[PDB]
Length: 88
Ligand SMILES: [Zn+2]
Ligand SMILES: [Zn+2]
Picture 1 (cartoon, protein in one colour):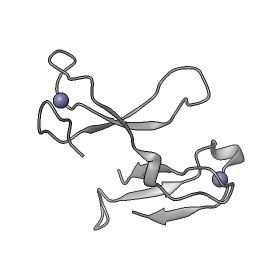
Picture 2 (cartoon, helix red, strand yellow):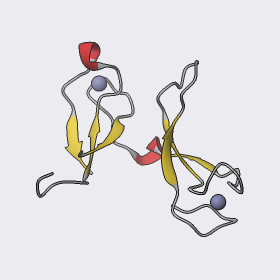
Picture 3 (cartoon, helix red, strand yellow):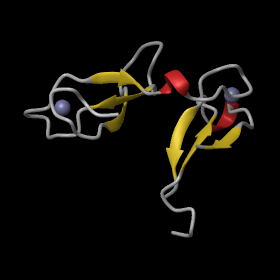
């Protein structure tokens, strides 16, 4: 997706704050903090559900052929993560 003011591909940011949505990913304007439009669109509205019944979180590969691809995992923290995995 792209913001509306600028027709530019959004970045995927993570809500780094406190509340019932810390860690939830959202598409936002890709420009520097200045000139950045106020675009904001929750990214996980179409993500798969992990085995807990919760919206999965998207990760990227950080060297081989499948470098750069996206996948989905349980969003709860290694200690309590379920075993859900799915390629995007
Ligand atoms: Zn923008
Ligand atoms: Zn889970």
